[PDB]
Image (cartoon, rainbow, N blue to C red):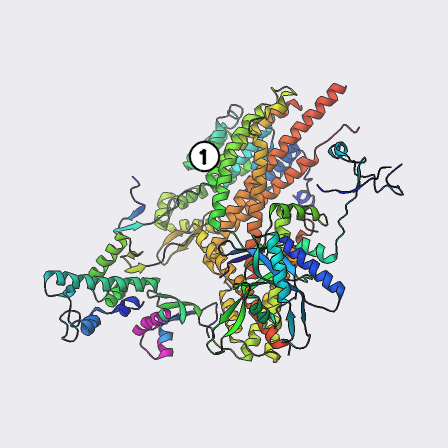
Amino acid sequence: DKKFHGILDQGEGVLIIFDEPPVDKTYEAALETIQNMSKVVDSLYNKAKKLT
Amino acid sequence: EKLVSKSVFPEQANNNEWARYLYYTGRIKAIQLEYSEARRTMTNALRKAPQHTAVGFKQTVHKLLIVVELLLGEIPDRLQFRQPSLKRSLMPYFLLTQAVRTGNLAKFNQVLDQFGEKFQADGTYTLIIRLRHNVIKTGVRMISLSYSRISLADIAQKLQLDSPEDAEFIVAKAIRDGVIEASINHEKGYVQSKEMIDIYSTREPQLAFHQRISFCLDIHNMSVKAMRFPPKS
Amino acid sequence: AVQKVVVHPLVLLSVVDHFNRIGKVGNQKRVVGVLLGSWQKKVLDVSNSFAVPFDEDDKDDSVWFLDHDYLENMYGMFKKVNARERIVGWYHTGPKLHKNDIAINELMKRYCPNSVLVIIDVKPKDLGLPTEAYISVEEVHDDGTPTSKTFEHVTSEIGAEEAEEVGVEHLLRDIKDTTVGTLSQRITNQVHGLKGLNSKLLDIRSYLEKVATGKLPINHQIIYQLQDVFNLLPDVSLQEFVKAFYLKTNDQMVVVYLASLIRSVVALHNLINNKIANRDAEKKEG
Amino acid sequence: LLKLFTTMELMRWSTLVEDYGMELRKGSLESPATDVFGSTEEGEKRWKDLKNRVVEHNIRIMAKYYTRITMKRMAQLLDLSVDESEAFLSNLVVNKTIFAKVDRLAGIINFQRPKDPNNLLNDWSQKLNSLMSLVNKTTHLIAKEEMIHNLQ
Amino acid sequence: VIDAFRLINANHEPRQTTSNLGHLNKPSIQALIHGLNRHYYSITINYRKNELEQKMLLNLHKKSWMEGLTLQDYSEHCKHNESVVKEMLELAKNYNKAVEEEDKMTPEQLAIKNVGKQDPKRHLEEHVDVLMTSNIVQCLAAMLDTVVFK
Amino acid sequence: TRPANHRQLTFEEIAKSAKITVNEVELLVMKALSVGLVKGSIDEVDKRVHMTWVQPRVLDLQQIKGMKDRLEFWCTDVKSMEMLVEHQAHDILT
């Protein structure tokens, strides 16, 4: 349920506790921008039909 | 091969010519034992082929790609096997991939005997014959992908082989070939898979991004030089 | 204690004019004068200045003369013309500190207790600011024992009002090159910074050569500061530092790559539009 | 006693009780004692609180100096059992007085926070800036020395 | 805006022309209305300078050397990069929307289309320029420091 | 004495040098840090001390000459990088 950041190590009977920055928030924005510009390039492909 | 090695293909060539050249070079490298380069070049060829037309070229490149991927020991994606254009043509190769995945020499021989003539017609019978004997490579790849440390007896049991000596020899061959990143240890008798290195901390991302940055800058420069202002004519 | 000294461009140009006129008169090497200004809670502001008669013997560092009667009269007139400016310090164009400077500062402290000296090099053979600010302070030693009056550095910068900025920009039609982009971010820094660092290190090397050969005696404080510098010099082969450097570089190159992709798509859009326009124009003309 | 508690060095409860144990508790006729540490239950509680203060001071000092220590050594230096030292450190960490991480399996107490790449690069940049400032100051001192010793 | 003047007596031409230097200024309408070339005449202003004046004027804007090599807090740098990329995402959405137009637009309507409305292409170009400058400068400064300081 | 790049002493070495048992090394180093002679940290788990700064001391002329040589190396590196940047970016900065 993500109450605390940690992981269990069975067999050894341990509980590891760590702090994590799971996401960058820059890579995600870059990926979304890449998708949006893929759509833009698709629109450019459509517009280039007038050249033909 | 000699002509390809000694001649430098023009970089400012049409995408169709690039597709043809990539297909032929991949064919040559696949007939020789350069499966990795063949797969790379032929993926590039299929990528560069025209989107709508060139149906036959797409079928040919797809068949060769299926065979070379099977030889390398991977599993081709199933999406290409249901496209309306490449549906009926690739059925024998679909069955071949099925047999390779669920490795069974009975099924493989049945498929080969049935569609023997079409493989000859399409130009992949010899490669399929090679696959028929290097099939186990796929099983070893799946075992390496799944298990972090397995015993040679267990590998023999999973690969339906004879005494673990044959399994050890096969695994050593694969490791030398580079199919699997693992090390054998007979003082205990198990194969241990190597660790996964942190690729980001390495300089590799810098190299990839530099390549792509240079490509984008070249695209912009050439797209600005392509401009024409004609009123002074 | 002063945290910063702001010297307006009019002060610098007035210093240059004073130097030029006294030089045209002849037989002089350094010029001296007063720095009228104002205080802004530990951030000084030097706005105006006026010349003051001054002479010195080139051999004796104890025969110098400054006309404080003229200083007082001209200060009275400048106050009558602009009340908000009060004496703040003195300036001299000598390339480097002279030995009479502490005495002159003691004289000027009777007009400004917190007097600030500003040396303006009117012939700068270097790459950097033309103003150096010093404040007189008592120095207590541990082995040097007698407490002497030494000059302590204070950060100095150049600022301007709106009229002064307008005038300077108008007059700067000598060599104008703004190029605020990567070009200026490469010339105003990087190259300039490395050249200045090389100059400072060369000065330190010259002093160390003189000390080692025996022209100058040893200064334990300078040697200690050099030890601290060489200790601060970091190590760049540590695995942790290398890994962090690679991580940050990868992030920066990600952003750069995305920007370049945007640029390429915009260029393609422009090419398509231009080709459409040219084809349409040719069709219409036909 | 004030100097002992202000100096940043380890102190021992046994040594404190030996030296100041009687002066601050029973007192002497020349300097009478105070009700701070009397024989009543209030005084007993205050004595226990002083012991806890000594332990906290020791932990703070061994956190100012020390990147990693073992639990056995921390107990040996605090004059308490391993369990008691662990409880004390855990209470301090929970109350947020000091930063510590206990690796019970290895018995290690880590006093250094995680180092982000941003933090490492910022430290390197700060070192470079300090180096440049020191170079400038050294140049100023050199100029002063040359002025003083060069004219003659 | 500065000019120099002198008067004309009650007389003919006020001055003699032995060159083109005088007739290069195109006197302003306001000065002509208020009496230029009728009660007074202008004189060209020139800004001859000496070497030291030139050098000081050029040196005014020069910054300290350490400022050039000084880096920039990496937390702040990353935050700025993140903010600009997040903005570029929405700008890319709007750019996709705008590209679909420009075909259903009158040749005159296009000019007034960008009046009171954001221009995704222009903003994307500006953001690209700022990001490229900042990141290139930071990387180059980092490498230069890495070598210079041991 | 130890070079700047290692500057990572060990408990046994300190004990041998100062003629004290390994146990008192921690207290000795802590007293040094408290007084302000040296700056660093103590890692009991690995039994090491990471010294990052020792107090300045008076140096003789041979050591001054060594400092001069180190400055020579540093200045050579600075000049090399300045020349590299100038040559490579002459196109944008003329």
Query: Which residue is depicted at the point 53% across and 80% down?
Result: F60
Query: For the C terminus of chain D, which image quadrant?
Result: bottom right
- Callout count: 1
F57 over E127 or under it: above or below: below
**C239 shown above or below B131:** below
Q: Residues within 10 Å of mark 1 (few under 14, many from 20)?
A: many
Write down the quadrant of residue E105 in the picture.
Answer: top right
User: Residue B146 vs residue E68: left or right?
Assistant: left
Which one is in front, D148 or B15?
D148
Nearer the observer, C8 or F80:
C8
Label 1: chain?
Answer: B
Amino acid of disc 1: Phe
Magenta stretch?
A: F15-33
Q: Is residue C127 visible?
A: no
Left or right: where B159 falls relative to C30: left
Per the image, the residue denoted by label 1 is B108
Q: Residue at x 75, y 35 (%)?
A: E31
The secondary structure type at the circle numbered 1 is helix
Question: Could you tell me residue B168's position as x and y percent?
Answer: 41, 51
Give residue D64's position: percent from left, percent from top.
34, 63
In the image, residue E80 lies in the stretch drawn in magenta: no
Q: Nearer the viewer, residue B63 or B225?
A: B225
Q: Position of residue E25 (x, y in %)?
A: 79, 38
| Residue D90 x, y percent position in the rendering | 25, 55
